[PDB]
Amino acid sequence: KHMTTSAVNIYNISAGASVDLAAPVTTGDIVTFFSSALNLSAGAGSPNNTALNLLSENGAYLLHIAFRLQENVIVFNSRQPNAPWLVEQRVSNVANQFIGSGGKAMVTVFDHGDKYQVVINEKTVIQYTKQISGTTSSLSYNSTEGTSIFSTVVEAVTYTGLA
Amino acid sequence: HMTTSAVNIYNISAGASVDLAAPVTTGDIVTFFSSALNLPNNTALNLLSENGAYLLHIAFRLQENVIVFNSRQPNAPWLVEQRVSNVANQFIGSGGKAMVTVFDHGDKYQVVINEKTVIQYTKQISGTTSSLSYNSTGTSIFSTVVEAVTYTGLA
Ligand SMILES: CC(=O)N[C@@H]1[C@@H](O)[C@H](O[C@@H]2O[C@H](CO)[C@H](O)[C@H](O[C@H]3O[C@H](CO)[C@H](O)[C@H](O)[C@H]3NC(C)=O)[C@H]2O[C@@H]2O[C@@H](C)[C@@H](O)[C@@H](O)[C@@H]2O)[C@@H](CO)O[C@H]1O
Ligand SMILES: CC(=O)N[C@@H]1[C@@H](O)[C@H](O[C@@H]2O[C@H](CO)[C@H](O)[C@H](O[C@H]3O[C@H](CO)[C@H](O)[C@H](O)[C@H]3NC(C)=O)[C@H]2O[C@@H]2O[C@@H](C)[C@@H](O)[C@@H](O)[C@@H]2O)[C@@H](CO)O[C@H]1O
Image (cartoon, rainbow over all chains, first blue to last red; front, side):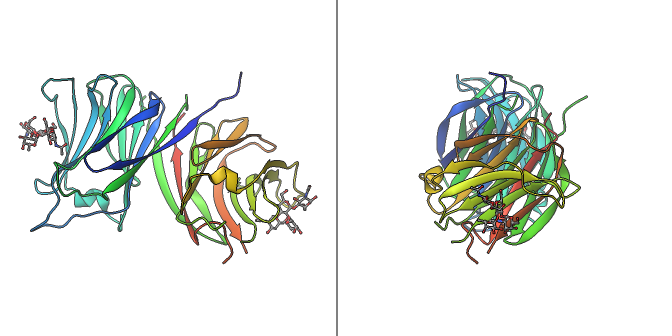
């Protein structure tokens, strides 16, 4: 065959849950996490640190995106299976990254081979140089066993077979 | 030398159009998100070129029970229709929302409803998409506002 066939896959990921991808994400592909909520409140009941993750088949964290309200930073990192975290990249001021977001948000990751480009709504927040390479085979959503900055269910959409 | 891609988000009301800040070209994607599924009069989602050609017209026709795909030049007649039968069957397990994705593959538009490819549409007019539109009679099959997301600067 000569024509290009791409694919859309849709996943509902609860806080504290993971999904295995039916179509892996590789160079040229995209994943967007859609949240139907955004909670940036301080004080009692304030959200715990909340992460969205792209994992390889052996459980490496290819990209970990940790939104830390109290510390007021977004941390980007990677981690081999059963190993220490690698070198963090940080973006300061969580709320500033969600200006004009309203009551929902999206976090998009482009796999560009050597880098992951992360875009919050329309704003590129990092061109992250990869610390671990390879295909993404699962996604996960960690709210430190408690209150999340996002909706209880986040919808992940993958666009694959692009290249 | 690095690739910089872009996400753009548009809120398109029924009977409205939006100009794209970043045009959709070969390798790019547009997804239309509806927060309702009303399965209502004929409803269309359109990709238009700078000169007002309909590069892709997607018409959902509930009563006729078909989805019609076509193109047309500015100020000119419609071209050759491609049809997909049974509208509801394309939205199996959709619930109360839906998404319609168009991949610009250069020679074809691949249209995917939720996860299901419904057509590999052979282009009848080529070129970049510079605007989107959403047509209906309050009788749309989709929500009054549809959110379009474009992914551009891919290739
Ligand atoms: C200034 C500085 O360098 N600080 C470092 C901290 O940021 C490190 O904290 C960990 O950072 C990781 C990313 O680099 C990651 O976010 C991790 O939390 C996540 O992973 C752990 C297991 O390692 C747990 O599973 C957590 O639940 C999980 N959290 C989320 C939201 O996904 C961070 O570690 C946790 O948070 C910090 C603040 C401490 O409370 C730790 O005890 C927690 O485990 C830190 C360790 O790499 O190193 C510092 O130097
Ligand atoms: C079997 C066959 O060939 N049938 C043909 C019909 O499908 C043709 O209907 C038009 O089809 C067009 C795509 O090929 C297009 O969907 C069009 O409607 C759209 O464009 C018109 C202007 O031309 C209006 O702007 C409509 O509002 C717009 N529709 C939407 C949803 O945005 C179709 O024409 C309309 O719908 C049909 C069913 C009739 O009611 C027409 O009078 C309407 O104008 C048809 C005409 O090209 O030719 C048949 O042979």
